[PDB]
Image (spheres, coloured by chain):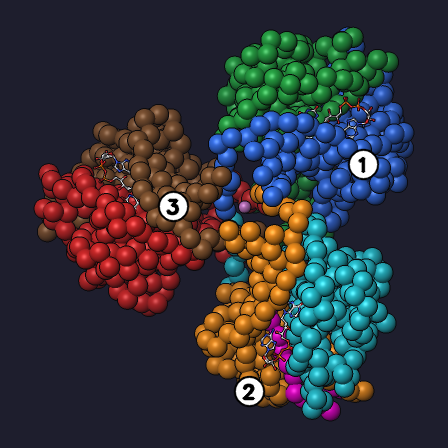
Chain colours: A red, B brown, C orange, D cyan, E green, F blue
Amino acid sequence: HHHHHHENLYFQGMKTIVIEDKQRIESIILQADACFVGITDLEGNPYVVPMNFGYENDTLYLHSGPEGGKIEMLQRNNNVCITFSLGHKLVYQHCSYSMRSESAMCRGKVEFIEDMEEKRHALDIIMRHYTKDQFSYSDPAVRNVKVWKVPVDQMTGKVFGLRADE
Amino acid sequence: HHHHHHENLYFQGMKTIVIEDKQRIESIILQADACFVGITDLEGNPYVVPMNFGYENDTLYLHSGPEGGKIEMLQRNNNVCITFSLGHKLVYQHCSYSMRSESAMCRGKVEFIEDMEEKRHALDIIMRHYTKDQFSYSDPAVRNVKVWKVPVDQMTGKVFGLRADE
Amino acid sequence: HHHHHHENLYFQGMKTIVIEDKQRIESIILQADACFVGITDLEGNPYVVPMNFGYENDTLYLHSGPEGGKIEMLQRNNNVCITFSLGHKLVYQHCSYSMRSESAMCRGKVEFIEDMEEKRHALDIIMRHYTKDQFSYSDPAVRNVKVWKVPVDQMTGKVFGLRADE
Amino acid sequence: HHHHHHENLYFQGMKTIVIEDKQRIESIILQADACFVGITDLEGNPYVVPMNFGYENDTLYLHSGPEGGKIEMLQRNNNVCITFSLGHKLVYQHCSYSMRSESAMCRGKVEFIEDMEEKRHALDIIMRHYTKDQFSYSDPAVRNVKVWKVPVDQMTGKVFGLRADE
Amino acid sequence: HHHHHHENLYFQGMKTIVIEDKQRIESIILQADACFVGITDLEGNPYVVPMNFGYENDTLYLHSGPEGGKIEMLQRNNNVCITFSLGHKLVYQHCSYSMRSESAMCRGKVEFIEDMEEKRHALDIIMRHYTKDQFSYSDPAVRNVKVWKVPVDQMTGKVFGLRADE
Amino acid sequence: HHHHHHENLYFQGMKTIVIEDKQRIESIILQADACFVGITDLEGNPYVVPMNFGYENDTLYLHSGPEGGKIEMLQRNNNVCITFSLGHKLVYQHCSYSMRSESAMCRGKVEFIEDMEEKRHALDIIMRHYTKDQFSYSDPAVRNVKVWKVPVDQMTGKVFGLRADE
Ligand SMILES: Cc1cc2nc3c(=O)[nH]c(=O)nc-3n(C[C@H](O)[C@H](O)[C@H](O)COP(=O)(O)OP(=O)(O)OC[C@H]3O[C@@H](n4cnc5c(N)ncnc54)[C@H](O)[C@@H]3O)c2cc1C
Ligand SMILES: Cc1cc2nc3c(=O)[nH]c(=O)nc-3n(C[C@H](O)[C@H](O)[C@H](O)COP(=O)(O)OP(=O)(O)OC[C@H]3O[C@@H](n4cnc5c(N)ncnc54)[C@H](O)[C@@H]3O)c2cc1C
Ligand SMILES: Cc1cc2nc3c(=O)[nH]c(=O)nc-3n(C[C@H](O)[C@H](O)[C@H](O)COP(=O)(O)OP(=O)(O)OC[C@H]3O[C@@H](n4cnc5c(N)ncnc54)[C@H](O)[C@@H]3O)c2cc1C
Ligand SMILES: Cc1cc2nc3c(=O)[nH]c(=O)nc-3n(C[C@H](O)[C@H](O)[C@H](O)COP(=O)(O)OP(=O)(O)OC[C@H]3O[C@@H](n4cnc5c(N)ncnc54)[C@H](O)[C@@H]3O)c2cc1C
Ligand SMILES: Cc1cc2nc3c(=O)[nH]c(=O)nc-3n(C[C@H](O)[C@H](O)[C@H](O)COP(=O)(O)OP(=O)(O)OC[C@H]3O[C@@H](n4cnc5c(N)ncnc54)[C@H](O)[C@@H]3O)c2cc1C
Ligand SMILES: Cc1cc2nc3c(=O)[nH]c(=O)nc-3n(C[C@H](O)[C@H](O)[C@H](O)COP(=O)(O)OP(=O)(O)OC[C@H]3O[C@@H](n4cnc5c(N)ncnc54)[C@H](O)[C@@H]3O)c2cc1C
Ligand code: NI
Ligand code: NI
């Protein structure tokens, strides 16, 4: 493994570019291990919490314990902004340095699924994001989890390029 | 490379544990490539934006273009929640499956640094997070960037363990 | 990195499974760095040659010098079987050992594209398989390469599982 | 990890070079996870099938179920061309781009080993290519596999270099 | 993965630089998987033996069987030089080639811990260097190992840079 | 990537095994990035210094500045013990934990090559250990380096296995 170092790089733009292609945005979502869920707290300030997730058919699924911090907040305002990003890559253009990454952002409202069988279905979507293993859930386990359904009302993607030239 | 698959895993708890050790929380921050900045939007809903950053001496530094989306929001409410996380690891206990990750969260208020030399200093903290290369910034480049200073008022860390047993 | 060794494994089946999903077969093709081109030689015996390639719209593209070995053969019989495979993965089922891989196979006939502009187009499909860089081709370079077009008449995929149990 | 991209690359030669050194060709064979077996089908056209293998003392060993597709073909013509290749490497010469790989090719005739103990011996050569684990084979397992012995009559190696310059 | 090759590199200096920062030297020690223990043999010549180790609070811990080669030597001279190094990195300065690594060196004297409980404590420091797993040690296992304690009297670090220019 | 953790492991033996096969010992040497050179210091105590190296035909080659620390020592006693090791691997036997590595050790005497052309030859052996690039050496560069030749009088290899069982 090797590195390229420069003595005389001059900082320049960053430009973001919008990703239009829905499959490409979904690809980012599907590649991500965690997501960052923004919730407005009880004082009107941001709260960002990382969480595991599943995604299918314009819908995000999460799960948590049944209380409290983020739960109290969602009960007051259930609008969430869920953001995803993969690491940056470093690209040298031939000289020129560019550090590039991409992200997805989903906005929607949180429901807590109550039906026991719907909860299992959703829990399966979440687990399938991380393993091919078969999961069972006892009734008491399904009872002691809140399963979040977030139909995605707006889904966007962005490429960010941070640039420097010699 | 190899994988372990099970036919009969039963979902169980997730538990979060609080990370008290400040150096350990800072280690997470220092390991992270990007951070997820939560801002309350103009309607009171969450907006989470990934961004590059630097961290030193209980202070986060970011930079952006001088407008608009996130800028308009910060001008109305400059409280931000900035969250960091490293990938999950998979641990098999010997049977038992555990998927474990850790995160940091910083809460503080955003200033936009106006002094040209302070802006360069801060830009250096940000760049040093990603490379050892020396960056210069022309005056016009320093002018055309907003450099965000976020003294961290509360910094917390959390380990999350998602568990299943045979 | 770690390994699991067993003292008492008993060899069992191999089973192949057919992959029906065309996008999944194309995914294998798109993941592969090289392909293995089977040509019948002048005596009726197999000749398998690895080659770089591009794939779009049920068509494979290759390129070579304008002579000789494989060229003489194709001039007598231009039917080729082009095969692709990704490495094996090792999966332990929980005990049981399974070594699993997947492959694609395309059958079609080889044309040598003569039009200079068609040759460039095809050469672009091939290069785009390996890099995002822009390639130019002088006229003399386009002249001194044979560009193979292989419309795919049959495309199949297979998963192979080699199994052992304790 | 980083990438180098160019705006103005001009495609040039590919050259193959012959690898004379037998130990070097055997090294390629020994590094490979799978091999691509070319068989002439019943209509005289190529059939290329990937397969696992072992190699010792100028002899390749494979195994399969006792029927059918490739078996019917080998019963008509047991000449096979078995080809191996490792991934390409990318080399920048300092500018100049070169994508380089190497391959081996073995030509020989297929026997199906009938003696039960010879079959086990050969199966061991194959397994030792992939693991250090001890494999047993019940009699019924040895019965229900065809074990292919292919003394190698011609073994060749080739380095291929695909080149572009600025 | 890619490589950069040059036709016309001119060998130049190597320079070592002293690492003053104790935490940085300890970081090297903590990163290392093995250490190389120098012992003067019975004829006055060097003997360098690799070994696993633990490090805490300016003290190195090792363990071995209770005899013989290195044991006889230490009984005559228990001064040891224990050296650590991480792989080299390759850095291209933009042209210029630099191959850089770092090492730590600890000098101290070896005791063999006799108290059974002290031996377990030390064995724990060693194991914690390699895994988070809980180890037990039967009395007979603790008896049949020599546990080496080496208070570090001098600890130094060095960066070595091997350089070539175009 | 995943890990296996145990609650109840019992420490056991370490056993070393002697590696007899000269090609296998040379393979370890050839795989190593650095070597650890033991020299007896001026007081009769060990000094272990890491260094780059080349190996061909039972001979090790190193290079350094023309002074001082290790040079003064070698002028009094030019016997060196040069040791090599590759990382450990972790092997789970199926339960049982084994951490395994291998090392080589070469004993010989150090000459400093004086002839300018011999020095270049040797410097080439060293560089070829790390890159395929062509190195030149001006006369003044060859003058300002000591090139060490160490015909290997004894070369040995050892596998070390550190074991724990459930
Ligand atoms: C990548 C990864 C995946 C995760 N997946 C899930 C999951 O799917 N479901 C789930 O319930 N949890 C998950 N977690 C943890 C998730 O962030 C927790 O729900 C959260 O930490 C507890 O949520 P809360 O709002 O109820 O916290 P509370 O206990 O109500 O808040 C207590 C306080 O602790 C601090 N805090 C809370 N969360 C974090 C954070 N993670 N990092 C640093 N400080 C924090 C804040 O100061 C907060 O106000 C995951 C964590 C990681 C790192
Ligand atoms: C890891 C990485 C690092 C980055 N580092 C920086 C940096 O340090 N400084 C910086 O200014 N930018 C950075 N970006 C991009 C940062 O997220 C942008 O500032 C943001 O995308 C534009 O911000 P804004 O609020 O001004 O967007 P606006 O242009 O005001 O918003 C337009 C709309 O586009 C969508 N959108 C905005 N951001 C995203 C997002 N990134 N993902 C998906 N959809 C989005 C939303 O629907 C938004 O309302 C980075 C991006 C990545 C992925
Ligand atoms: C992965 C990789 C990618 C390649 N991509 C291309 C490409 O896209 N275009 C291209 O033209 N070539 C490519 N090659 C080389 C391709 O295999 C050559 O065209 C081939 O080696 C020469 O083809 P031929 O039939 O004209 O050989 P000839 O020179 O006519 O045959 C001479 C003899 O040498 C031996 N031989 C030929 N090919 C090989 C082989 N590769 N391995 C071992 N022995 C061999 C055989 O005994 C053969 O009969 C690639 C090679 C590798 C390893
Ligand atoms: C790397 C890896 C290693 C393998 N190792 C072995 C092994 O050692 N022994 C073994 O018996 N098999 C192995 N296989 C599978 C080997 O390719 C099968 O024997 C083959 O797929 C079935 O062979 P056949 O000629 O009897 O097929 P048949 O069932 O007779 O043919 C049916 C049809 O299915 C299609 N087809 C057949 N093979 C493939 C292929 N693999 N890819 C895409 N389409 C195909 C063709 O259209 C073919 O005509 C391996 C597969 C992979 C990917
Ligand atoms: C990285 C790794 C970690 C290790 N960790 C430990 C550990 O913590 N504790 C421990 O006791 N051992 C460990 N070993 C092995 C350690 O080097 C042995 O103690 C040593 O090999 C036997 O030591 P000795 O002086 O008692 O050898 P003896 O059996 O007394 O010497 C016999 C002769 O064999 C040769 N020889 C000895 N050691 C080596 C060597 N390793 N490489 C090549 N030839 C050799 C020499 O010619 C020596 O004179 C490790 C080995 C590796 C490679
Ligand atoms: C893997 C790597 C490869 C190297 N390859 C070479 C090479 O081939 N040629 C070469 O000349 N040097 C090389 N070095 C450095 C080699 O170890 C130096 O020669 C050495 O550091 C200076 O040697 P000396 O005996 O002349 O030191 P001196 O300057 O005479 O000693 C000064 C003091 O500094 C300390 N010290 C010396 N060496 C080290 C060490 N490396 N680690 C920690 N403290 C130390 C000791 O306390 C020593 O007594 C390499 C270093 C690394 C890490
Ligand atoms: Ni590079
Ligand atoms: Ni494992």
Q: Is residue A77 left or right of residue A121?
A: left
Determine crowd level at label 2: few under 14, some 14-19, many 20+ residues with C-alpha closer than 10 A.
Answer: few
Q: Amino acid at mark 2?
A: Asp
Range of magenta residues: C71-87
Q: Is residue C72 magenta?
A: yes
Q: Residue at x 46, y 39 (%)?
A: B93
Q: Amino acid at mark 3?
A: Ala
Residue at the spot of label 3:
B164
Q: Is residue F42 left or right of residue B44?
A: right
From mark 1 to mark 3, how far is it between C-alphas?
Answer: 44 Å
Q: Residue at x 54, y 72 (%)?
A: C17
Determine crowd level at label 3: few under 14, some 14-19, many 20+ residues with C-alpha closer than 10 A.
Answer: many
Mark 3, secondary structure of its residue: strand
From mark 3 to mark 2, how far is it between C-alphas?
Answer: 47 Å
Q: Is mark 3 within 8 Å of ligand 1?
A: no
Residue at the spot of label 1:
F19
Percent across and percent down for residue C31 are 53, 66
Label 1 and label 3 in one chain: no
From mark 2 to mark 1, how far is it between C-alphas?
Answer: 56 Å
Quadrant hosting residue C147? bottom right
Determine crowd level at label 1: few under 14, some 14-19, many 20+ residues with C-alpha closer than 10 A.
Answer: some
The chain carrying label 3 is B
Q: Nearer the viewer, residue A91 or E60?
A: E60
Residue at the spot of label 2:
C153
Whether residue B71 appears in this view of the structure is no
| Nearer to us: label 2 or label 1 | 1
Q: Is residue B78 above or below residue C160?
A: above
